[PDB]
C-alpha cells in the first residue's frame, strides 16, 4: 500500500471512466468497463479478513459476467448493421441484452443481490469510490444509446428497483445496507427518466453523488457501523448531529431542503407526458424509502441514547481526522433549493 | 504558558494564508476584469 | 461427397464444449475444453483465417495449463466426478447432447429453425470470397494495422496489462 | 434537446454568448451564492472546534470568492442556454406558418358556455 | 404475454363467457408460475418433491384467484349488463381477496386482500374504460 | 483436411499400438497388480488429496506474459508500413512496458518466494 | 430531569443483527467490530509420503 | 446466414447457463467463463472474416487478451479464497450475509 501505487490505481480508475466518456468505438467502452473493474478490486481487500475476500469474489463474478454479456450485445450488433459508432442500435434483441448487462452492472432489483453484500464488509473509502465511479460510468453509456431502447425494460427495472430499494431498507440495522438500498432507490429514479429527458437523469446523478459524498464523509468522521455508534457521536460532538439531521432529510428529499430538486423536476419533465399514474406510484414509493432515514435520525440526535464512558477520555482529543471535503459539499447539497434554473448548467 | 509538550497549531503558518489570499485577490482581479470585458463586449456587438 | 464440413466441425465443437460447460471435475472439463479449442481452431482455419486460430489455440491452451495447476492445487475430492458418475451431471450431459442432435435434425431434414432468428439452413460455402485478388492474405495486413494506425489502442492495452500485473502482485501480497 | 454546437462540446461559452447581457452586479442569485459561501465558511469553522466568525476570515474570503466565481460562470451558461432555446423556438415558429394555426379568438357576445349552476 | 392479455381485453363486454374465465385462469396461472419459480429458486426446498408441492400450492391458489375472479366478472356482467361502471370488477376484486383468505384460512389478511384487490381491479377497469395509456406516450 | 487425413492415419497407428499392447501377446491374471505403488507401503487415502503449491505469482505471471507474447507476435507483418517511426515508438513502448512490469515484480521480490 | 429518555430496552431493539426477527433469526449472528473473525482453524495441514526402501 | 453463426450462439447460451448455475466449484465457474470467452471470440472472428472488415481486426486479439487477464484476476481471487479456507464450495461462502 505505497501511496504511489494507490495514486496509480486511482489514476487508472480515472482513465477507465474517461475512456468510457471519450470513445465512440464500442470495444473501447467495453475495455473501459473492464479496466474500471480491474482497478476497483484492490481498492478493496486492504483488510485481511475473508469478509473482503468473499465480497470481492461476489463482485468479481457478477461484474465480469455482466461485461461478457455486454460483449455479446455488441457482437450481435455487428452481426447486424456493421458499425463501430456509439449510436442508435438496430436490434431489439441486442438492446435488450445490453440494457440487461448494464442492469447487472449498475444494479437493478433482480440484479442487486451483490450490492448489500459488497458494501457490507469493505472499508469506507472503497465503498465511496466504487459508488461514485461505478454509478457514474454506465449512465454515460445509457445517455449515449437512449433512443433505441425498448421502453418496458427500463421502465420495469426502474419501478422494481424503486420498490425493492424501498422495501428492503426497512430492516437493516447496519449502516452500509441502508446506504446500499438508498443507492438502489436513487438509481431507480435515475433510470426512470432516461427515455424522456436525460438532463434530469444526469442532474439526479450529480446530486446523488454529492449526497453520497457527504454521507460517506460523515461516516469517515467516526468509525461507525451501527446506530449505537451514531448515538455515541451525538454524545461526543454536537455539529455532527445536526449535519446528520439535514443530510438524512435531504436524502429523503423534502421541499425546503435540496433533495427535492431532483424529484420535482423529474415529475415536471415526466408529467409533461401523459404518464401520471405511474409517476405518482413512483413518488408514493419515494415516500416509502424514507422511514429508515427517519429511524436513523431518531437514533442519532432526535433522541438521546445512553453512551458508554471513556467518552470522558475522548473529550480531550478532538476529531483531528482528514476530511475529503465536508462543508462545501454539505451546503452545496443542502441549501440548493432556489437554484432550479441551474438545471440548464448541465445542458 | 499552560500547555504541555505540543502546540499542534496556535502559531499559524506563514505560507498557506499568504498563498490563499494571493490567489484569492488574483481571482477577484480577474473576475472584475471579466465583467468589464463582458460589458464592453455586449456594447461592442450592439 | 461431404460438403458441410465447417458445420460438422461446429457440431463437434458444440458437443465437446457443452460437455465442458456441464461442469464435471475440471480435469475432464479441461479435456473437453482443449478438444473444443482445437476443433474451433480448425473451424476458423478452414474458414479463411490464417494464423489467428492457431495463435488463440496456443494462448487459450496456456490459460488452461495454469487452470489445471490450480485445480490440482485446490479443488480435490475423495473421488472426483466424471460425466458418468453422478445423476445430475449425466442428466445435463444427455440433455445438452439431445438439444444438439435435435438441432442437427431440424437443420438437416427440415427447412427452418427460428429460435431467435430465421436461420437459413443450408451449406456454408455461401457466403464466401468470390475469388478476389488478395496477393497479401487479408488478415495478415488486418493484424498488421495494429502497429501502424493503432496508436491509442495498444497504449491502453499495455497500460491495463501493467496494472493487471501489479494488481495480482498486491492481492497476493496483502496477507 | 441536443446540440446546436455538438461540434465543440466542451465549449462552455461559445462565440454566440457574446451578444446577451452578462450577469450584473448585486443580482439576487449571486448574492445568495455569496451568502451560501459565508454560511459554508461558518460551518467549516464550526467543524474543526475553532470559534465561529473567528480565525477563519481568510477562509471566509476564499470560500466566498470561489463560490461567486463559479456562480458567475454558471449564470452566464444559464443565460446562454435560455437564449439559444428561445431563438431556436422562434426560428421554428417563423419556419412553418400553416402548421401552427392562429385561432379566431372570438368575443363573448356569441361564444356560448354551458353554465350548470350551484344552488 | 401482451398477446394473451390483449386477448383478455379484446373479449367484448359483450359476453363470450367461460372464455373470458379461461383467459383469466391463464393469467392467474402464469402469475403463479412466476411467483413459484422465484420462491423455489430462493429457498432450496429440500427436496425436489417438496418444491413441486410448493409450486403446486402457489399456482393452485393463483389459478383459484383467476377462476373465481372470472366467474364473478361474468356473473356481474350478465346480471346487471352495464360495462360502464367498475362496480362489477370491484365485487370481483373483493371476491378474489376473500377467496385468497379462504385458501390461507386467515380472516384479517383476507379482508385486507378484499379491500386492496377490489380497489385495484376497479381502478384497472376505470382507467381502461376511461382510456389511460400502457405506461408511456412514449413521445413528448 | 490433408492434415486431418494425416491425423486420422496416426490415430489408426495409435489404435493398432493399443490393440497390439492389450489383446494379442498373452494373458492378464489380476488381483494385486491393480494396487497403487509408492515405495512398498500402501499410502493413506489415495492421491487426489489436497496438495498445496509453492508458486502463486509465477503461474499468473506466465499467463500475463503469454498474453503479451500474443500482442508482440505481429511484429513481422508490422515491419512493412509507411509510418515507420510510429511503429518503432509503439513497439519500443510495448517491450519497455513489459520489462518495467518484469523488473517491478523482480525488485518487489515477487519471485523471491517458492518460485 | 422528568424529560423522558429512551432506554436499554430501546437500545436492544435498535441493536443486534436485524430489526424484525423471524423464526430464522438465530442464524443471523451479531457481526464483529473489527470485521475480522479471529478463530478459524480446520487443520488443512501437511500431507504424507513414504519415500521408502528400494 | 451461414449456419455456423447459429451454432456458436447455441454454444454461447449453453456456456452462459453453465456459468450461471453451478454446483460447488469456483474453479469450474472460472473455467466456463473462459470457455464462453472463447465462444464469443470465434463468433466475432467469423463475423469479421465474412465482412472482409480488415481495418479494425483488432477485435479478436484485444478482446481475448483483456478477457484472459480478467481470468487471471479471477485465479488470484480464487487463490485468496482457498488460502482462507480448506474447502471452497458454496459452503464457506455463507458469511457476510445478505
Image (cartoon, coloured by chain):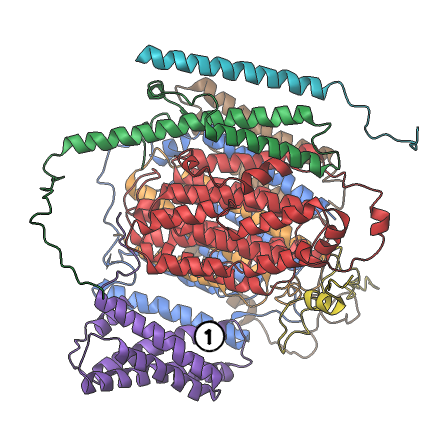
Chain E colour in the picture: purple
Which colour represents chain H?
orange
Q: Identify which residue is drawn at 66% across, 56% down.
A: A302
User: Color used for chain G?
Assistant: yellow
Residue A78 visible in the picture: no
Considering the numbered disc 1 on the image, is that residue within a helix, a strand or a loop?
helix
Colour assigned to chain B in the rendering is cyan
Residue A73, x across and y down, in percent: 38, 50
Residue that label 1 marks: C91
Q: Is residue A14 left or right of residue F30?
A: left
- Which quarter of the rendering shows the C terminus of chain H? bottom right
Query: To which quarter of the image does residue E102 belong?
Result: bottom left
Where residue A331 appears, as percent x and y from the top left, is 58, 39
- Give the quadrant of residue A178: bottom right
Q: Which chain is green?
A: D
x%, y% of residue C97?
40, 69
- In the figure, the shade used to draw chain C is blue
Which one is in front, H48 or E57? E57
Q: What colour has chain A?
A: red
Amino acid at each position: 500500500m505505497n501511496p504511489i501505487i494507490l495514486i496509480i490505481i486511482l489514476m487508472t480508475v480515472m482513465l477507465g471512466t474517461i475512456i468510457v466518456m471519450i470513445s465512440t468505438h464500442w470495444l473501447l467502452i467495453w475495455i473501459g468497463f473492464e479496466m474500471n473493474m480491474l482497478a476497483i478490486i484492490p481498492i478493496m481487500m486492504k483488510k485481511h479478513n475473508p469478509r473482503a475476500t468473499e465480497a470481492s469474489t461476489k463482485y468479481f463474478l457478477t461484474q465480469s459476467t455482466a461485461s461478457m454479456l455486454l460483449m455479446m450485445a455488441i457482437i450481435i450488433n455487428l452481426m447486424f448493421s456493421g458499425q463501430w459508432t456509439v449510436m442508435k442500435l438496430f436490434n431489439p434483441m441486442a438492446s435488450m441484452l445490453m440494457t440487461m448487462a448494464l442492469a447487472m452492472k449498475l444494479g437493478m432489483a433482480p440484479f442487486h443481490f451483490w450490492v448489500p453484500e459488497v458494501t457490507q464488509g469493505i472499508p469506507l473509502s472503497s465503498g465511496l469510490i466504487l459508488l461514485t465511479w461505478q454509478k457514474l460510468a454506465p449512465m454515460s453509456v445509457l445517455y449515449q444509446i437512449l433512443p433505441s431502447i425498448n421502453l418496458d425494460l427500463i421502465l420495469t427495472l426502474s419501478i422494481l428497483s424503486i420498490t425493492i430499494g424501498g422495501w428492503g431498507g426497512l430492516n437493516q440495522t447496519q449502516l452500509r445496507k441502508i446506504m446500499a438500498y438508498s443507492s438502489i432507490a436513487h438509481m431507480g429514479w435515475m433510470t426512470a427518466v432516461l427515455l424522456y429527458n436525460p438532463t434530469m437523469t444526469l442532474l439526479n446523478l450529480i446530486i446523488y453523488i454529492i449526497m453520497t459524498s457527504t454521507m460517506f464523509t460523515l461516516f469517515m468522521a467516526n468509525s461507525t457501523t451501527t446506530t449505537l455508534s451514531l448515538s455515541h457521536t451525538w454524545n461526543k460532538a454536537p455539529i455532527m448531529t445536526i449535519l446528520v439531521l439535514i443530510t438524512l432529510l435531504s436524502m429523503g428529499g423534502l421541499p425546503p431542503l435540496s433533495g427535492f430538486m431532483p424529484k420535482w423536476m423529474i415529475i415536471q419533465e415526466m408529467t409533461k407526458n401523459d404518464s401520471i399514474i405511474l409517476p405518482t406510484l413512483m413518488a408514493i414509493t419515494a415516500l416509502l424509502n424514507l422511514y429508515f432515514y427517519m429511524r436513523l435520525t431518531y437514533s442519532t440526535a432526535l433522541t438521546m441514547f445512553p453512551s458508554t464512558n471513556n467518552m470522558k477520555m475522548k473529550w480531550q482529543f478532538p476529531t483531528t481526522k482528514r476530511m475529503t471535503l465536508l462543508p462545501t459539499m454539505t451546503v452545496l447539497s443542502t441549501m440548493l433549493l432556489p437554484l432550479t434554473p441551474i438545471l440548464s448548467i448541465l445542458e | 504558558k499552560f500547555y504541555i509538550q505540543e502546540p499542534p497549531h496556535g502559531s499559524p503558518n506563514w505560507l498557506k494564508v499568504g498563498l490563499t489570499l494571493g490567489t484569492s485577490a488574483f481571482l477577484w482581479i480577474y473576475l472584475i476584469k471579466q465583467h468589464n470585458e463582458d460589458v464592453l463586449e455586449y456594447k461592442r456587438r450592439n | 461427397m461431404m460438403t458441410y464440413i465447417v458445420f460438422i466441425l461446429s457440431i463437434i465443437f458444440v458437443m465437446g464444449f457443452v460437455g465442458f460447460s456441464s461442469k464435471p471435475s475440471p480435469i475432464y472439463g479441461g479435456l473437453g475444453l482443449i478438444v473444443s479449442g482445437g476443433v474451433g481452431c480448425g473451424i476458423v482455419l478452414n474458414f479463411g483465417g490464417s494464423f489467428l486460430g492457431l495463435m488463440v489455440f496456443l494462448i487459450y491452451l496456456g490459460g488452461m495449463m495454469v487452470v489445471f495447476g490450480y485445480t490440482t492445487a485446490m479443488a480435490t475430492e475423495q473421488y472426483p466426478e466424471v460425466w458418468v458418475s453422478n445423476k445430475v451431471v449425466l442428466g445435463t450431459f444427455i440433455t445438452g447432447l439431445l438439444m444438439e442432435f435435435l438441432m442437427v435434425y431440424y437443420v438437416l431434414k427440415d427447412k427452418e429453425v427460428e429460435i431467435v432468428f430465421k436461420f437459413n439452413g443450408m451449406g456454408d460455402w455461401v457466403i464466401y470470397d468470390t475469388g478476389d485478388s488478395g496477393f497479401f492474405s487479408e488478415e495478415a495486413m488486418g493484424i498488421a494495422a495494429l502497429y501502424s494506425y493503432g496508436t491509442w489502442l495498444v497504449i491502453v492495452t499495455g497500460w491495463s496489462l501493467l496494472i493487471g500485473v501489479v494488481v495480482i502482485m498486491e492481492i497476493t501480497r496483502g496477507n | 434537446m441536443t446540440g446546436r454546437q455538438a461540434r465543440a462540446p466542451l465549449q462552455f461559452l461559445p462565440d454566440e454568448a457574446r451578444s446577451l447581457p452578462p450577469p450584473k452586479l448585486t443580482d439576487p442569485r449571486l448574492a445568495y451564492i455569496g451568502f451560501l459561501g459565508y454560511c459554508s465558511g461558518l460551518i467549516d469553522n464550526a467543524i474543526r472546534r475553532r470559534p465561529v466568525l473567528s480565525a477563519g476570515l481568510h477562509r471566509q474570503f476564499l470560500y466566498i470568492t470561489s463560490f461567486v466565481f463559479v456562480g458567475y460562470y454558471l449564470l452566464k451558461r444559464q443565460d446562454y442556454m435560455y437564449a439559444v432555446r428561445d431563438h431556436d423556438m422562434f426560428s421554428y415558429i417563423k419556419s412553418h406558418p400553416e402548421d401552427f394555426p392562429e385561432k379566431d379568438k372570438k368575443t363573448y357576445r356569441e361564444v356560448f358556455e354551458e353554465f350548470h349552476p350551484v344552488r | 404475454a401482451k398477446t394473451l392479455l390483449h386477448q383478455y381485453w379484446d373479449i367484448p363486454e359483450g359476453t363470450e363467457c367461460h372464455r373470458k374465465t379461461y383467459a383469466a385462469t391463464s393469467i392467474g396461472g402464469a402469475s403463479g408460475l412466476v411467483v413459484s419459480a422465484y420462491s423455489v429458486a430462493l429457498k432450496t426446498p429440500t427436496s425436489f418433491l417438496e418444491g413441486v408441492a410448493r409450486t403446486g400450492r402457489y399456482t393452485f391458489t393463483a389459478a383459484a384467484i383467476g377462476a373465481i375472479f372470472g366467474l364473478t366478472s361474468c356473473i356481474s356482467a350478465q346480471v346487471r349488463e352495464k360495462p360502464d361502471d367498475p362496480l362489477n370488477y370491484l365485487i370481483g376484486g373483493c371476491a378474489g381477496g376473500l377467496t385468497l383468505g379462504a385458501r390461507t384460512r386467515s380472516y384479517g389478511i383476507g379482508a385486507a386482500a378484499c379491500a386492496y384487490m377490489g380497489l385495484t381491479a376497479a381502478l384497472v377497469k376505470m382507467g381502461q374504460l376511461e382510456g389511460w395509456k400502457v405506461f408511456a406516450e412514449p413521445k413528448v | 483436411m490433408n492434415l486431418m487425413i494425416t491425423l486420422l492415419t496416426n490415430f489408426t497407428l495409435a489404435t493398432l499400438l493399443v490393440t497390439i499392447a492389450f489383446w494379442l501377446p498373452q494373458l492378464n491374471v489380476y488381483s494385486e497388480k491393480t494396487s497403487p505403488y509408492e515405495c512398498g507401503f500402501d499410502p493413506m487415502g489415495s492421491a487426489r488429496l489436497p496438495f498445496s503449491m509453492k508458486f502463486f505469482l509465477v503461474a499468473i505471471t506466465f499467463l500475463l506474459f503469454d498474453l503479451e507474447i500474443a500482442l508482440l507476435l505481429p511484429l513481422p507483418w508490422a515491419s512493412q508500413t509507411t509510418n515507420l517511426n510510429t511503429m518503432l515508438t509503439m513497439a519500443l513502448l510495448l517491450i519497455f512496458l513489459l520489462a518495467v512490469s518484469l523488473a517491478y515484480e523482480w525488485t518487489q521480490k515477487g519471485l523471491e518466494w517458492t518460485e | 430531569a422528568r424529560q423522558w429518555q429512551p432506554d436499554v430496552e430501546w437500545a436492544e431493539q435498535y441493536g443486534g443483527a436485524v430489526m424484525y426477527p423471524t423464526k430464522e433469526t438465530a442464524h443471523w449472528k451479531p457481526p464483529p467490530w473489527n470485521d475480522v473473525d479471529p478463530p478459524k482453524d480446520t487443520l488443512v495441514s501437511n500431507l504424507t509420503l513414504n519415500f521408502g526402501p528400494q | 446466414m451461414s449456419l455456423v453463426y447459429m451454432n456458436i450462439m447455441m454454444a454461447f447460451t449453453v456456456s452462459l447457463t453453465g456459468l450461471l448455475m453451478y454446483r460447488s466449484h469456483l474453479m469450474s465457474s472460472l473455467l466456463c467463463l473462459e470457455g464462453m470467452m472463447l465462444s464469443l471470440f470465434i463468433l466475432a472472428t467469423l463475423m469479421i472474416l465474412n465482412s472482409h472488415f480488415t481495418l479494425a481486426s483488432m477485435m479478436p486479439i484485444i478482446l481475448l487478451v483483456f478477457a484472459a487477464c480478467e481470468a487471471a484476476l479471477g485465479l488470484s481471487l480464487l487463490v485468496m479464497v482457498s488460502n482462507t479456507y480448506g474447502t471452497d464450495y458454496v459452503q464457506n461462502l455463507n458469511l457476510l450475509q445478505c
